[PDB]
Image (cartoon, rainbow, N blue to C red):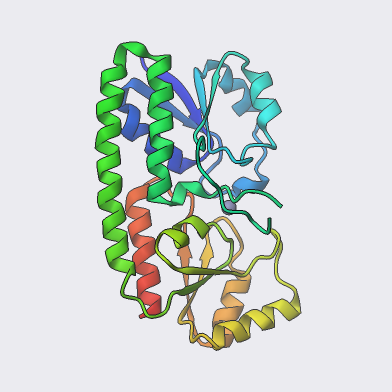
Length: 255
Ligand SMILES: [Zn+2]
């Protein structure tokens, strides 16, 4: 009975569960502990794709590397581009920043696009997808207000992270994300120092790393500038509670 849908990353399963509930059965391509930017789908996964009725793309080029392989594995599945209508930020002007799933504001748009496409695929349950969408959009506004309350009073708006997956989140809440990685690469020995000074000159209290990437340089920086080390997980499946934990971590660090 349920529609088989595959999504790219764990957070999307959260969005799909909220929008589809029991009407969909979700599979996920990228493991929560892998760097999605260098992930290559496994043969057993491409085979399983033949069962899929639809595939939900983050879009903005996020899936560019696997796109041809997904289409060849299943030519009948609908590709849902969840980034439709969204104006992206650029990562050094080469391309769009694809981390739109960490902005509650932009997720409202992704959710609307997804529900609209699912209702086209499964017209008989259109009313349920619409009601489920409405429930999820209201939850998103409430989450947005909650995150804004946690972050608006910070005098320190800057935070250092290893991998820059938080540019949209940061724009939403007026934070400044200072990344350690450069062009998907570990910092130079010089850059590391420069980054260390930057961090010293701003009195930063904590350095964040991400589970999917080595925290080696975040740890070295923290040891050198007198800070602690915390993990932020941009791929957490428990999306809403993870975002609140992220905001609290940032608030605790600038406090
Ligand atoms: Zn990323």
